Amino acid sequence: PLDFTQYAKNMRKDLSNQDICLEDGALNHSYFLTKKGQYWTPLNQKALQRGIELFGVGNWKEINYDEFSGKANIVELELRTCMILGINDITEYYGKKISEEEQEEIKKSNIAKGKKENKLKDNIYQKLQ
Amino acid sequence: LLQDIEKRILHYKQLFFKEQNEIANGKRSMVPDNSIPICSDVTKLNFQALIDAQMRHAGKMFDVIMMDPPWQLSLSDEKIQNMPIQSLQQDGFIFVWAINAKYRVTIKMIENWGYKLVDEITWVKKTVKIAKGHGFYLQHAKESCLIGVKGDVDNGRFKKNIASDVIFSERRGQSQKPEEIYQYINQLCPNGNYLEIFARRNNLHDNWVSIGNEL
Ligand SMILES: Nc1ncnc2c1ncn2[C@@H]1O[C@H](CSCC[C@H](N)C(=O)O)[C@@H](O)[C@H]1O
């Protein structure tokens, strides 16, 4: 005659760190699959996207200071950018600063291309070498 | 070989690409849904907030508490003793894991917080049946959980004679305690509020509050 599940929420709201649980007060499994301390927050995702628009792809050292101060594995960025553009080889786009409007298109375009080509895995287009 | 190395890297990014995608789709955490992890350092922690909320959403206080203090060889020994445990629970059991170095001190510690020592759980490490420990005077093949009580357990919630002093499990990623402790806690308290301090990520369970700086 206690609902533990509800009890969990309100506690989780005032007690647990913002990343740990959702606004409703449910607990977000994203935080718990990633290690540490290595969590990638929505908000700093916006920052990656913003960073590409300002400094361009493969500008991580310049991009890193501005939006992530330490802040991130150089790899995590490039891997995440591969995701933004929907390709798995990001080489083609390097050194180009791309607007958020356009990252959306490239991703949209690259994926459609992958799907028809029938070479898109995990929602990322695979690129021939 | 460059070709070999170049080849692996693409294969690798794909996993990551997949995992992030699965997460996007709702892939579950190992953690049970009902657990209530909190990340803090106890020294930093104000336990008032925890008490206010617990009283607020349960109108009750913890049935059980658990500890594996990070004994210095690393929180100051004084700091753990000085934690405001007494406020945290009013009518319940406490568990605490004492390395042989701290065994006496631990005793003095629970008594300090007003507990009465009533039982000790023993944990053996099985080869899969023996443990090799570099004991100072006798080699150690167990560590042990010291249990103390305060208040009325004559209450329905705690069930007497429901658990065994000895526990039998293999050691994983030590220091990681046997699963079966949480079962044994089910015997003692069935479906009642529990707490745990110094908690690591792996050991979270439903209905269990947990505080550690690694969460
Ligand atoms: N100052 C501090 N405040 C809070 N927690 C601390 C701390 N110093 C160390 N700890 C944590 O206390 C824990 C001791 S290890 C705990 C073992 C764990 N019970 C298990 O399941 O095996 C570690 O998580 C450590 O991160």
Image (spheres, coloured by chain):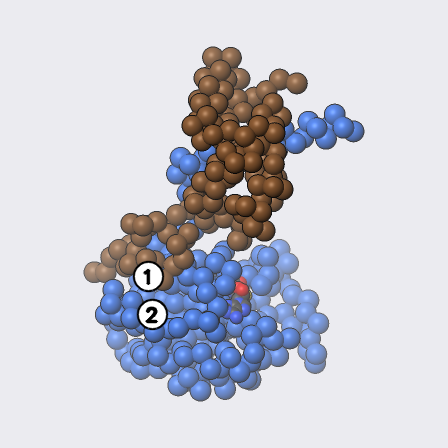
Residue at the spot of label 1: A14
Q: Amino acid at mark 2?
A: Ala
Residue B130 position by quadrant: bottom right
Q: Is residue B17 visible?
A: no
Residue drawn at (61%, 28%), measured in percent from left and top? A94
Q: CA distance from mark 1 to mark 2?
A: 8 Å
Mark 1 crowdedness (10 Å alpha carbons): few <14, some 14-19, many ≥20: some
Chain holding disc 1: A
Q: Quadrant of the N terminus of chain B?
A: top right
Percent of width and height locating residue B112: 44, 87
Residue B127, image x, y percentages: 64, 58
Q: Secondary structure at mark 2?
A: helix
Across and down, in percent, residue B16 comes to 55, 36
Q: Is residue A7 left or right of residue A127?
A: left
In depth, the one of A72 and B115 nearer the eye is: A72
- Residue that label 2 marks: B49
- The chain containing the residue under callout 2 comes to B
Task: Pick whichever, B30 or A115, lies toward us.
Answer: A115
